[PDB]
Image (cartoon, rainbow over the protein chains, first blue to last red):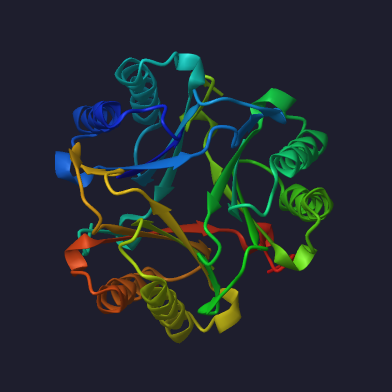
Length: 119
Length: 119
Length: 119
């Protein structure tokens, strides 16, 4: 999987980025069985003031986690993996759950390349 | 919904970002019935010269709006919501429709978390 | 199509960005038949140290290519287009295949707007 993680600049020190990528990655391997090195976490920073909720401009505390997964996971599984990302990122970032969004997009495995190799 | 809005740095003042998030958000609630606060608009700026159309490098006037929606919307509806985003962003940004791209990705609601809560 | 190409800041000079957008674009038109000007390549740069593989922090050499396509392409086709992007970007960027990830997301054409016009 590839987890696109959208945060504001300077809300996560370099040591907290690592804790959030670690939390996300572990949650994914512990609940799905996909090996460690197959989970990419790509942080996308933006300046404070680039997030809007109901047309209202936010500060720096929002995190949107967008996971791009292979298809074929029960709804039960994907829900557990979402809740666990919310909780684990919440601690690993020192941020309340309310500031944490999690979306999953699914793809056929045969159009999914990691390390230059197909799944 | 979450609308990832991809623009070049310094093409939208802070007051125009707000107008575009407002336009997008209103279009979504007026056509779908999802409440205001449930629509995130996340602007993603990049330097001028990071967009290519047919391998040809562009300036700062392109906007790509990528909406991430819950599944289960008629094709008629999604088309109206796309046209309305094109038109409303065009005015709210002072930019011609030709410079505006709009893509929607759909997801099951049960893998969709906002404010730390499932849909 | 729209190809979101995620790289680290200052790993691609401006002249290499153009070669990668050219490689991607040509691969897409040669294998699908979609005309040139319909392929957007949007580079998304981030600072070195924003990519994590298995919770381990990377330098600047990773490239994630995320294509957003219209639905309805055989699996055979999408695989050829993925391999060809891997190989062609590898040369056009001077980067080993191992550092290159490629994911495709598919959408209904009727929710897909380019140049302010529906597909």
